[PDB]
Length: 485
Ligand SMILES: [Zn+2]
Image 1: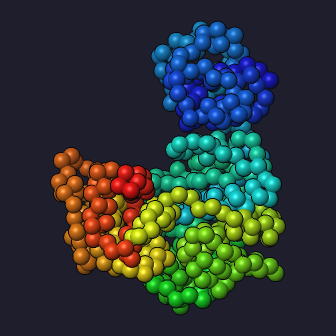
Image 2 (image 1 turned 120 degrees about the horizontal axis):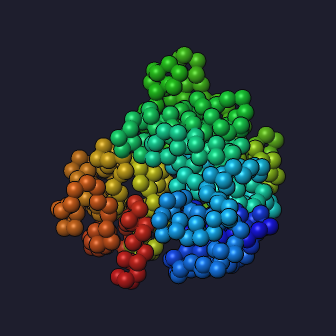
Image 3 (image 1 turned 60 degrees about the vertical axis):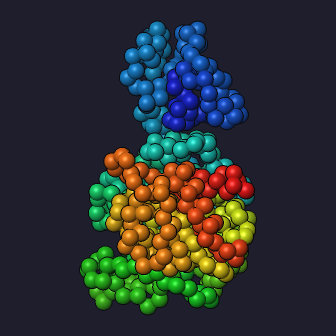
């Protein structure tokens, strides 16, 4: 119970440091040269007074302890101020990291589905009366460990990697992850690195998490399994779908894996002659249909009715379910959490009726495959691709080839245009994707997405579907359509 200043306490980490210290009972006040923060609402909500547009010397001087945001650990202007109060005690992020997390921490990792799994679980937990710490940020590595140190009952955090080694591991150990979840593994973030190296990065979660929630339908994820592992998966479909199959090699002997049934891409029921076989999942999805399936866990069975449907959403729901089960959450509550879950925007979002216009965050082969498998246009399919795969041209090409099923493909980014020359469908381009004046990757712009959408509307009938995929598309689609009305 002391007086603490948090210089640069409006930054991503500064904010969390501030809140954490405040949650231990302290006369906390944030000091920042910046005069604007979206965090004023949550700051005032938790009893953290502000001192923006410059630092109050009296504040700093009187205060007993001062916290410094990592991004300003060695800033002359800031240290010339911290040393105006030499007898005060310093609190850098390492000190806050020393703080013990005792709350159960659920860590979610994987290629796709992390966000939806995370929010589904957050819903399940919340309606069950459990406090989950929110970082309340508009954006790293220190976010997950610090978020988990915020007050609450159970922490649910995202631990991803661009493919950088020990990222997952360091952040997971620092978050004290007790329950480790892996949604799926596929090609993404492979800019310079190998797919193999990426998989090795993902395996890191299994080096810290005591318990593991693994996808049994993903051979690579499944092979990570230990003694404290709960597996989830699909046992059967009642609907017929397009496989979009992707090969997988046996992780133990290297031979190409044989599949007896396929659900989505590389997710299915597999086996190897060496003896490796898909584990029978205890958290399963029975009689899967588009927007309805029976979730079965031990002796319990409950009908899940999802708003946004699709096999990949079934998988997200299974992972969330499995995590909750590990947490001993009542079955009916797991069901309620799933059935009342509100899907995140940008996830198969309808933003126009005739023609149908959907926007979706899909940004890799697995994402495009998932939505293409789920989407069922009654009319034609016009795709507007704003994707500029972070892996590079190789996956862009793969995505374009996948997109060949589209009646029309309209590239909305430089990368997407470049890649579309290797696809076997009708390709209609726009001038904004014609010449890149600068070097290196240049993501889809508002104007490029604008031109592409207009071209799409120009070709679409009232009964057609225009699917807008990618970051740029989700980001500018609504306003482009609204300014066009
Ligand atoms: Zn094998």
